Each structure stands twice: as structure tokens, then as C-alpha cells.
Image (cartoon, rainbow over all chains, first blue to last red; front, side):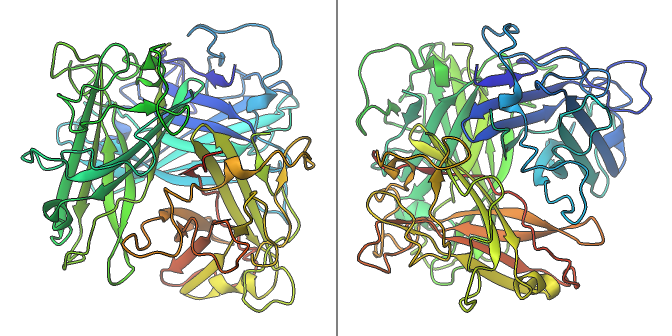
Amino acid sequence: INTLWTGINPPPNCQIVENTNTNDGKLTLVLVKNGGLVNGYVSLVGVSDTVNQMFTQKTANIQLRLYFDSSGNLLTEESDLKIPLKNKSSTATSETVASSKAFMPSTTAYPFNTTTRDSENYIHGICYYMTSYDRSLFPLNISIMLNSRMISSNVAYAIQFEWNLNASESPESNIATLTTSPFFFSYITEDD
Amino acid sequence: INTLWTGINPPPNCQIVENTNTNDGKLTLVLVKNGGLVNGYVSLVGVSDTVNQMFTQKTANIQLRLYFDSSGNLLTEESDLKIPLKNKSSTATSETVASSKAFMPSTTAYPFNTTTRDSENYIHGICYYMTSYDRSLFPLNISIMLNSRMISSNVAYAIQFEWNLNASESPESNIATLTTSPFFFSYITEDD
Amino acid sequence: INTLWTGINPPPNCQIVENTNTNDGKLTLVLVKNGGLVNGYVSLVGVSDTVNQMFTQKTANIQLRLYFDSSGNLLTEESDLKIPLKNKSSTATSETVASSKAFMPSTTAYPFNTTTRDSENYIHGICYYMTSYDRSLFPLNISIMLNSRMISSNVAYAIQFEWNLNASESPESNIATLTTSPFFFSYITEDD
């Protein structure tokens, strides 16, 4: 049960836009309990042509905000991911809510809405986008927020993924199925 | 047994130049089963005058292709690595064949030779090389394929590393035994 | 017991400057036993006024040198880290000197003071420093040396961290609580 994910290759379960009437992408998130820290693995695959065109320009920004409750269960209504996470006990969602907080980011490490302590609970790094026709690689800046702020009375934990493109003439086409490359990461996990 | 590796400080076990009939590099590969993911650790060291006199050029491309059978076993023949991977249980491999599939990259999140899913199963990142005389750092792109294509009937999985340099004037002498800094990756292990 | 650390959020446990009568930074370090590997986590925070004003220039290089005795305990004398690394069996240390070795960097994969092997035991990568007023990032260079050399007869293993700024005009203020973003690393653990 040391794993909590989206599933290997899942169906469209994102909402890359503050409008979209449905799911436009395909987030693949794999969290694994490693004692003190949690092991991250993140990768996005745009499903909606609207999201598949964003890159067509020269600069873009996609961010997905995830919110959990006090027991580490995804809150579909609040968070951009609209499909619950499950812990691989098959490849199918495992039952027995034995607490998923084990995968939750320590609020003592990653404090909520605090000043005189300014953010300093960010994850920064680079992932890459492989060009449609040409197989080139454009570096897109990725950063994980971690307990951004609780927008809801029922938000106890938060993990936010933000990809930022800012190059000179991205793939001008659409075959740009937009595929962010895997971004490996870790964060101090919540106590028990 | 969470560990499948090349062993600590192995002996020449690669075939880097697509020409050599002898091993010209020492590859260190360590895979550790961690829930639904597999923690990777690669580093490479040059052995032959040939390989070592590569960063003497402002441009290089070394690539190692590994192929395993349905039982997570390495195909020495089809691979550039000519020594089977072993599981930590001493510092010496452990016997029995409970199957090394648990370390094999899931052929569901990373499919084989087909279109409509054109690549997107690549892990791109950056590792470094630290000059001989001086102590300066050179960025050298790394990218891990993952089930490129079954170059043989008896191929179940494949993992291909690829170190590429592209700067302007690198340690041009020779002592350059060549050394990639370790690069850390993670992918979705095979079901079981 | 697979978690050796400083503890989520610690007290200035450092000694960056080769001067400071006392500590001046808050190093956050998490090691995790993981098969033949050790998954690391690193983030440093500036406490002193002197430190929090380094990034008021264009360059800087700070290095926390670490050393352990044959059983894997942090030798506070020789290190710039002045508080032993406790085991996580609460959020407060764990007893039973059943050995912390398993967390230590294999003296074989990473040898000590020697030639014919010069250096070749560094981990290089980039983490980031966010701007105080602007929400920008300035990439710094962190190298992890592993088993540098043994400066004392009681030195068994060592893990040296080095961060390096080398850009052009950094957050010239002081608000610079000097918070380096987390740096994920892995190294091959000592036999047992």
C-alpha cells in the first residue's frame, strides 16, 4: 500500500482550464511512501485540442491544483484532478480507508497561508516537451506548491503542479498532443 | 530483493562504440522496486582510450541499449551491456528466479513500436561531466527511452540510456576518463 | 527506522561561514534507506544576518562539510552541522545503536583520499533560490561530494554539500531568508 496514484495510463481526468465544461487532459501521478519522504512522479498528456494548441505559440502556463481532506482523500469538487486516487492493490483501487495521510505533505514542513515565513515550501525544476514533427526538446519550468492555501473549510492538504513554457516559437501545428516529460520529486510526508 | 543492479564498481561491462568487440566502459545501473515505481540510478565511466578521447571533442553521443526477456532477464547478446544484472542479497547476486519482472518498465504506460502514441515514453534530464585539470562543469543531456522496440523475438522489455554533449570546447587532453554524474529517474514498474 | 534526519523544521544546526562563533543556518536533511540506495532530500535556510546577505551580490559558494564515525554517527566536532542526526521513531529520535551505517555512502563506490580515482564521486544538479520581492528563480549549483577525504582519524564516511551562485544581480535586500529549494539525491549505501 506504499503507493497512491492515478493508475497506469488513465482516461481524461484533468481540467487544464478555468472554463472547460469537461476534462481536457490526462494527469499521471504516482505517489509512493518512502518512510520519511514521499516519492513523486508527474506527467501530463493534453486531451483537448484547446490544450493541444496552447503550445502552438511561444509561451504557455498550465497548472493543476489538488486538494485533499483530513484523511488524504482527493476532493474532486475543489481540485483540478476530477478522479479519485487509488492505491495499487491490483491496478484497481484498493479499499479499507486505513488513512491516506501517509501520502500527505507535512503541514509542519509545508505550512499553510503564512507570512514572515513566506512560501519557502516550493519545489522547482525542469521537465521537457518533445516537439511534434521535429523531435526537439523544449525546457518547460515546473514547480510544485504543496499546501498552497486551503480554499475550502474541508482542505487539509494540497499538492499543486505548475508547468511554464517560455521559449521562442514552440511547435506550430497541433499534433502537439502536449506531453510533459516525467518530473521526479519528493517532499517530507505528514507524520502518520 | 528490492534491488536489481550492476553491482558496486563493476568491471568493464559495456560496448559503447557501436564497433568494439571488447568492453569499453563501466556502467553502474541500480534499480530499486519502490511501490508502483522503480528508483533508478545511472552513472558511466570510460575505459578505452577511444571512449575517453571523446570529450576531447566539443560534441559526443554515447548510448547504451538494454533488452530483457519476459522474466526481466538481460539479453547480453542484444544489449550493449554484456553482464547480466544482479539482485542485492550479499553484494553478490542471489539465486532463484522469482522473476525480475518487478523491475521491468510497465509495457502499458510505455508501449512498443507503434504510432498514435509516438514516443512520449522518454525520460529527459541533465547530468554533468567535471573536467580533468580544471574542475568546471559541463551539461550533458541524458535521456532514457523505455521499451523502444523489440529488436528480437525474445525481447520483452528494453531500456535505452543516451548521454549527449553539445557545448564549446571540452577537456581536450585525455585524462578525461569521462564520468557522467549520477542521474536519478523513476518509472512505472510492470504489474508484478 | 528507514529515516535519518534533522527533523521536520530544525533549529539553526549549521555553521556555514568558516568564522561564526555559532550556527548561522538551518539545514534540513532527510536520508531514506531504500534497498541498495539512499534517497536524499536537502534544503538550507539562512539564520544569521551575514549569511542572509550573501545573495546580495552576483556570486557565492557555501559548503557544509559532514563527517561520520565507523557506526554512522555525525561527528559534530569536524562537521559544520552541530547536532547529531536522529532516527525517526516519533519525530523525536530512536535508540538502539543497531547501526546507522545502512544510511552511509559505500566507501567502495565512493573512495577516500586517493588518486587513479581522482574525484569521480560527486553528484551535481540544480535547485533554486526564489526572489524576495519578485517571484523569480535564480538557479544555483549544488554538488554533493560523498566521502570527501578523512580530515580526522575518527572519520569513516562524509557527505559534503556545496551550493553555488554565479549569475548577475541577485535579490539585493536581506529579506533573503536565503531559502534554497529542496534537492533530491540518491547514492549507493554502505554494505550493512
